[PDB]
Amino acid sequence: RFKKHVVQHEETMQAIAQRYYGDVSYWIDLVEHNNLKYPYLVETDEEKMKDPERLASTGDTLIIPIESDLTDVSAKEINSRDKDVLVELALGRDLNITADEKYFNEHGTSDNILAFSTNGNGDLDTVKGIDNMKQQLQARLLTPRGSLMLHPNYGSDLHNLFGLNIPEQATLIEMEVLRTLTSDNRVKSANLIDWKIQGNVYSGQFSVEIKS
Amino acid sequence: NEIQDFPAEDVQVIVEGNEARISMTVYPIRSFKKISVSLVYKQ
Amino acid sequence: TRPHASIEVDTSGISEKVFCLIGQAEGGEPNTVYELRNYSQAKRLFRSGELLDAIELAWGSNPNYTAGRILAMRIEDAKPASAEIGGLKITSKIYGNVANNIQVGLEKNTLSDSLRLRVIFQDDRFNEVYDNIGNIFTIKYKGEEANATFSVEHDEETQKASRLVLKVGDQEVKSYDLTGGAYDYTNAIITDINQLPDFEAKLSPFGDKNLESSKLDKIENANIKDKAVYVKAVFGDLEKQTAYNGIVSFEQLKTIEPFELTKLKGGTNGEPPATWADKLDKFAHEGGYYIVPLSSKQSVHAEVASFVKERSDAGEPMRAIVGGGFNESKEQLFGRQASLSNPRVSLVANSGTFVMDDGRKNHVPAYMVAVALGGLASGLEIGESITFKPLRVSSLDQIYESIDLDELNENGIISIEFVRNRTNTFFRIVDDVTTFNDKSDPVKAEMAVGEANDFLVSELKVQLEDQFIGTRTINTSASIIKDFIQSYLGRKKRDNEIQDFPAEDVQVIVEGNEARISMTVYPIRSFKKISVSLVYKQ
Amino acid sequence: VHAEVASFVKERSDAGEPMRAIVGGGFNESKEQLFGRQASLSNPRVSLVANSGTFVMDDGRKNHVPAYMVAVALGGLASGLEIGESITFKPLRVSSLDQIYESIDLDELNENGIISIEFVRNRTNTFFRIVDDVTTFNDKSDPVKAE
Amino acid sequence: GGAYDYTNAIITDINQLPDFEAKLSPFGDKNLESSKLDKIENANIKDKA
Amino acid sequence: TRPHASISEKVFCLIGQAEGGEPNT
Amino acid sequence: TRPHASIEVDTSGISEKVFCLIGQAEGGEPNT
């Protein structure tokens, strides 16, 4: 996996490699990972006009490998394709089934909710990257734990939790949400920011550390 | 644990001889009926 | 409705003080203040241009610190786009030129004897249709007289619905008042027809209409034995159909009539205003502290400066940070400083470039670097300085270097310095000096010291007020004032809001009509000179 | 009708019964329009209120309030306070108010006997307080009538 | 002498002959004793102030 | 002047030069 | 003053009972 960087004023190419790897000498590998010509960085943006794809300038974005994938030619090849789209390799692409967030949010835990839909024309709607991650948390959490017809212990116990509105029960809802969300490797961790018990409405908001 | 709370200061009482009258507030216990989660991203 | 659970993957945001921006942008209703708490709300209240790019910059100028809540105002007298087409006044909720792209049309359906409404607007990808406009409910009569009808009469004074009547031949079977009565919501008609023997009435299935009964239209003697005819009420159905959504509103001059899909007109941002003070007046009581105008014009800089001084005289301290032009010269800068040499103002020279989160490598004028700066300065804890803090600017269109960073700073003008590496963005801001001429006094001269003074002073004012200015009794002489003030100072030392104070150097004098106070405080402010010496024993 | 109330309070004073009236004026009144009321409402025991703002009413609605009703805010305050206590500098709990008048304006309205309102900034919170317990009366050396 | 010794009384009472107008200066307090005014005649008025 | 906040028994005598204050008082 | 650091390789290093000398030298204002 990788890190983003933003090129700064008169930024020395070797300073990038030092700043993230301690030794200077890995800049040969970094520029091969980013498919740069010899002018690795340039002050003037008009010079980029000549060879835009093979020439970077101030404020442009570069891809920094982690140390282990530094000398892997295959990673160099793939990292030469997915330039500023590399996120898509970790989070993935999947089919869209959230046809209207105005619909299922008002019906909640039930059968017969979500459905495939079509964006544009002819091509079936494929939802990707961060927008795949939105769906793959949302569609997971709405499913009850026992539900799915292979690999059980999917879903969540959330539908059980509509007990008495008293504080302990609210923390129990926090716990099942936390438990459900940290269950997928694409998220590092989760924690609660705030919660609000109305007379019969639970409201609470949670952070999640998506990777990259 | 049959009422959520009561603002004791709200209780207002009047007496009119051989009769009296009260006003009060109580926050009832209920089931939950809407659960709303907001889910937010980082870095 | 029924019990359920919801999960919104909120895109909001993709803390103590408040920050004020007045500038030019092409959306939002004019001459009213707004509080912005979320960038994703600013993209929806507003649309385009400096006021929004300023906010997108203010809440991102440092990777760890960021500005508080922002107060906004638009510096245009934008009209809303409108038209008179048919018998309807169509007016758009958008104010400005953008609203001219809106399209509205109407067509009548033969298969339901109703209108079909269409509204289109390009940049928000809005293009939706509402149908069966009217058709509010149907009646069929079921008795076996030859032919029965109903009627609905207006209030001729007001064109409001007055009665609904059922007629079998010449006999009034039943009637109901509609000028208010029992039947103010249509629901009670939907029972009180059905409950009779000879008639039944039923609703259309497309949503709950249940309109206010005064909105029906004048009809007389419509057959409802051979047919299950609609009651129409075509105008008031539009509110139930479209009021809560979208971009357009409708108002009546007259009869509603179909028309082709037609554009609006008159959406006009107008000339820019020749003066900003009249609109600057509105920030006077919204609770700001730091204010920046988004313009290089010298008249605006003088008006804002005089406005800040007027507020400071009236119990509300304020401070203005201002930039100028695209890469100004020393002669221009010292010309602006000499004309504007009052305190509570600070002038910024450079014009930078920022990587705007669209991927937009924006070259940005000086009055916008003042936003990026003012945003950072506003967000930090009280009493800290911008002194030697970094800024997330990409590159600079600049003249000034180390020797100039004596000249400009010494004359009270702020500028950003290039440091070649490791310090996050390679750029840090040299000082927090103000535009005031005399640098000897630090409260006037240096911004952070003033910003700590202004809130400390307000607290001493507010706490003295209810203890003494309330005039609860004269029988509390000056010795008690020393007790209260030393207690007050002892809290501030304990709370770190001051460095230290001498307790036995307080003098109080009183004459019953007025008390006089004297006190000394040792202030807290950022280091600025570090002289570290070396010695050795060889 | 303000003159009638002033006559009524004067008539009850002659009857030996103490009463006092608090009164407001229009929307967005200027200094001079208020001076015209002040001169025409000369006697003591009548208290003129200036500005017209907004209050958060029971509904949760942003109700617009004329000076005729802003007078009620001070009336409800002066009747709640202990006898002999000053109305000066107590909070007012006003959501928004046509209150551009500045510190020098407060001195001009106060000297002429017109009750004014002020914006005050705490450390971070803010609040609006009323700046003097003055009446519509002229004489500065007669606090029994001027206050 | 009398009620009109302070110009405030005239600033009020000109606006008790409401075909005319008088209005105050914005630039701070003045409260001038009217005996200190200076002699003037026949300035041409309707539109003008 | 509305109300606001704004922010030894052996007496000793002297007589000499000074660049200020009215003399003979 | 400009906000900055500074550094020195000092040379001025090379008890209570104060000590007095008087003699000839080609410097200093006299008698003091």
Image: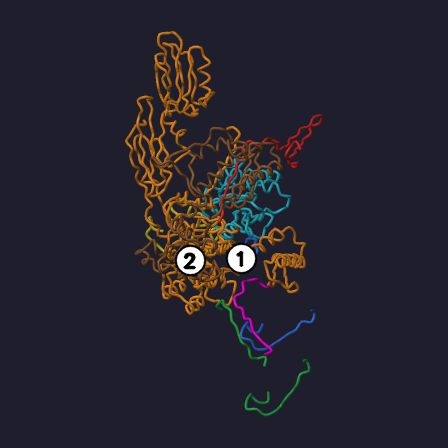
Chain colours: A brown, B red, C orange, D cyan, E yellow, F blue, G green
Q: Circle 1 — which element? A: helix
Q: Is residue C512 left or right of residue C50?
A: right
| Residue D139 shown in magenta | no
**Which residue is disc 2 drawn over?**
A29
Q: Residues within 10 Å of mark 1 (few under 14, many from 20)?
A: some
Residue situated furthest front in the rendering = A73
Judge whether residue E22 can be spotted in this image: no
Does residue C161 lie above or below C444 as drawn?
above
Q: Residue C268 sits in which quadrant?
A: top left
Q: Residue at x 40, y 18 (%)?
A: C164
Residue situated furthest bottom in the rendering = G24
Q: Chain of mark 2?
A: A
Q: Residue at x 40, y 38 (%)?
A: A126
Give the percent coordinates (x, y) of residue A35: 37, 55
Q: Residues within 10 Å of mark 2 (few under 14, many from 20)?
A: some
Does residue C51 lie above or below B16 as drawn?
below
In this view, the residue in front, C89 or C533, is C533
Give the percent coordinates (x, y) of residue C91: 35, 36
Q: Is residue D115 left or right of residue G18?
A: left
Residue situated furthest right in the rendering = B18
Give the percent coordinates (x, y) of residue E35: 45, 57
**Which residue is disc 1 drawn over?**
C454
Q: Residue at x 31, y 55 (%)?
A: A49
Residue type, numbered disc 1: Asp
Foreground: disc 1 or disc 2: 2
Residue type, numbered disc 2: Asp
Magenta-tinted stretch: C522-538
In this view, the residue in front, C469 or C3, is C3
Does residue C429 lie above or below C472 as drawn?
below
> In this rendering, do the residues under marks 1 and 2 share a single chain?
no
Q: Chain of mark 1?
A: C
Q: Residue A38 sits in which quadrant?
A: bottom left
